[PDB]
Image 1 (cartoon, protein in one colour):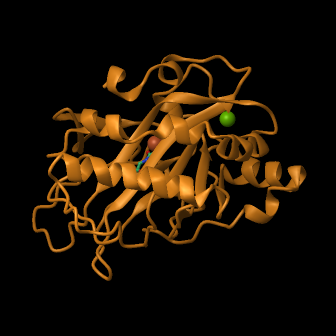
Image 2 (cartoon, helix red, strand yellow):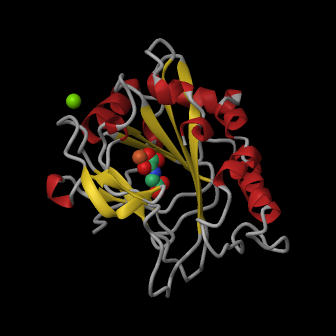
Length: 264
Ligand SMILES: O=C(O)CNC(=O)C(=O)O
Ligand SMILES: [Fe+3]
Ligand SMILES: [Mg+2]
């Protein structure tokens, strides 16, 4: 169902008019090699440390060789102890990028979601229920809708290893219908997702390979979903994290102020 690549918006960063115009029309920005790659490597290594320490991964493996039997069998709460995301998001170099995007001082959510998904290529009964269906972060984050989601790869993604796919320009008609879907679950219970019918033909589904150092960010009403990891050439974990950022002056709601483990 993916029809296109993200547009490389990096050349827009030093042109406020063009940057704002693209974001207004499209509801996303794809920025390449703007984050400190050594900082990103450190986060990736921290995630690996967790997966190794918790018995899921091989201590002899490089990041790209890394694999785990199952996302679900890893203690996610313990993983949050390993991955030092707040120190990353709030590093002056990272903040500089966020500030250039918003054009004003920012506040980074105290909640981050960390994702460490093995390839399930070849699996006859794959476990993809922990992924996300089509949704808008604004459906469950608020009350303010001026936050943006910041999504980063910790190791590179491919079209086959997955990531997040975005319905281009789908952020301009408010929140769309999220209905119960038995194939997506959290805590063993079904979750709500936007049926593909509620996404227009013109709202092209974009997903592109990304490299550590890149950022994908998007509007509260941007309709987006997970792309499953079916990598085999080469087989890669999909290792990423996502938080939300907003203007420093905006109201700070429940998710803004509450760490992932607390709300989980
Ligand atoms: O990364 C994924 O699979 C899903 N991510 C999101 O829904 C997000 O970052 O808002
Ligand atoms: Fe989301
Ligand atoms: Mg609107």
